[PDB]
Length: 42
Image (cartoon, rainbow, N blue to C red; front, side):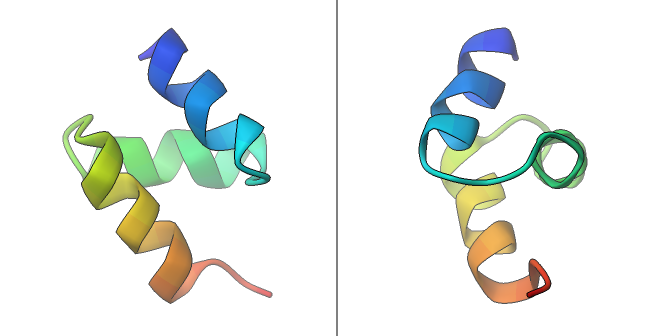
């Protein structure tokens, strides 16, 4: 998870949205990324 959080924050996403997307995604990074793309606000 720590590598996955770092990957996604390195891509510009914020800490709390990253952790929650990973939770919903059951730690699938590709799925978490798709969640962030579709649903992050702004």
